[PDB]
Amino acid sequence: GSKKPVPIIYCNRRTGKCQRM
């Protein structure tokens, strides 16, 4: 065990477009 799953959301406040991944 070394790595760990973690879904990071991408919020593009610059282009007014956020997402989850």
Image (cartoon, helix red, strand yellow):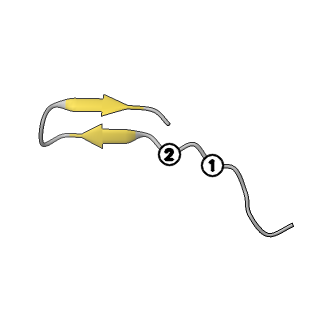
Q: What amino acid does circle 1 point to? A: Val
Q: Judge whether 5 appears above or below 21 on screen.
A: below
Marks 2 and 1, how far apart at CA: 6 Å
Question: Vertical placement of 1 versus 4: above or below?
Answer: below
Q: Position of residue 7 (x, y in %)?
A: 57, 42
Instruction: Say which residue appears at 30% left-offset and 32% top-offset.
Output: 18
Q: Nearer the viewer, residue 13 or 5?
A: 5
Residue at (36, 41) in percent of width and height: 10
What's the residue type where badge 2 is placed?
Answer: Ile
Where residue 21 sits: x, y (%)? Answer: 50, 37
For residue 12, above or below residue 18:
below
Report crowding for label 1: few under 14, some 14 to 19, many 20 or more residues within 10 A (C-alpha). Answer: few
Q: Which residue is mark 1?
A: 6
Q: Quadrant of residue 2?
A: bottom right
Which residue corresponds to mark 2?
A: 8
Q: Quadrant of the N terminus?
A: bottom right
Q: Secondary structure at mark 2?
A: loop
8 horizontally vs 2: left or right = left
